[PDB]
Amino acid sequence: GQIQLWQFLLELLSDSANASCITWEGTNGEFKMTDPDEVARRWGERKSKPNMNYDKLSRALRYYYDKNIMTKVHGKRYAYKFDFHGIAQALQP
Amino acid sequence: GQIQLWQFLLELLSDSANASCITWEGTNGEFKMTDPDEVARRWGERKSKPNMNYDKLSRALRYYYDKNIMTKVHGKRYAYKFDFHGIAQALQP
Ligand SMILES: [Co+2]
Ligand SMILES: [Co+2]
């Protein structure tokens, strides 16, 4: 059904078989997209939106910064951090 | 519906109207039970297990240590920390 981008990333992150494109790395919440192109592609497939690429995926994450769901780590690139404040709220109907 | 203990605490944590019994405090994932007795009571009601109390609630959480869902902050009391490793896995069917 209707799965959301943040949920998709935790799905990918939940299995180290996906490490070639995405993996936890760092302290609580921190991950890196080892292949952002591949992560965008897989999302596009899942949400049957085959116009999806990395630029569009990066834009959609921007929405999540103001919701406190996650935040981009400035300085590093392709690095991000899930925040429990917003995730706990996003987890609610 | 049938809801899980870790799921229940995130629900409570999602709303600061519950601060009198449970609140985020600290860095990513860190929380403390301002009223552990109240938290156990509300759980018992939710899972229709009216034998529930703090001692049993703290037992149930110990299960989550080896699942990496959460950990107890040693040296403090009633302080805990949700881990995104285990949570990402717990969200999976
Ligand atoms: Co936060
Ligand atoms: Co961890």
Image: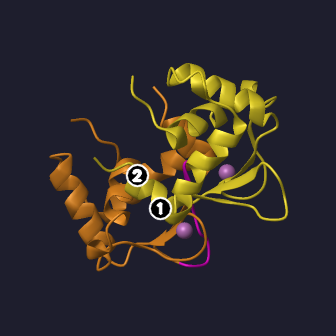
Chain colours: A orange, B yellow
Tell me the magenta residue range.
Answer: A69-76
Task: Please report the residue visible at 55 percent of the width from the left and 34 percent of the height from the top.
Answer: B8
- Contact, mark 1 vs mark 2 (Cβ under 8 Å): yes
Of labels 1 and 2, earlier in sequence is 1
Chain ID, mark 2: B
**Residue A16, magenta (yes or no):** no
Q: Main secondary structure of the magenta part?
A: loop
**Label drawn at residue B67:** 1
* Local SS, label 2: helix
Instruction: Decide if ligand 2 comes within 8 Å of the CB at mark 1.
Output: no
The tally of labels here is: 2
**Res. B74 image quadrant:** bottom right
Picture residue at 36% right of the left edge, 72% below the top: A22
Give the amino acid at mark 2.
Answer: Ala
In depth, the one of B47 and A39 nearer the eye is B47
Residue that label 2 marks: B90
Residue B93, above or below A76: above
Observer-side mark, 1 or 2, equals 1
Q: Residue A47 shows which numbered tag?
A: none
Question: Which quadrant of the rendered structure holds the N terminus of chain A?
Answer: top left
Q: Quadrant of residue A34?
A: bottom left
Task: Decide if residue B51 is on the left or right side of residue B48.
Answer: right
Where does residue B45 sit, x and y in percent of width and height? 58, 19
Residue sitting at 40 percent across and 52 percent down?
Answer: B90
**Is residue A72 found inside the magenta-colored segment of the image?**
yes
Residue at coordinates 59% horizontally, 28% vertically from top-left?
Answer: B43
Quadrant position of the C terminus of chain A in the picture:
top left
Kind of residue at disc 1: Lys
Q: CA distance from mark 1 to mark 2?
A: 9 Å
Q: Are marks 1 and 2 on the same chain?
A: yes
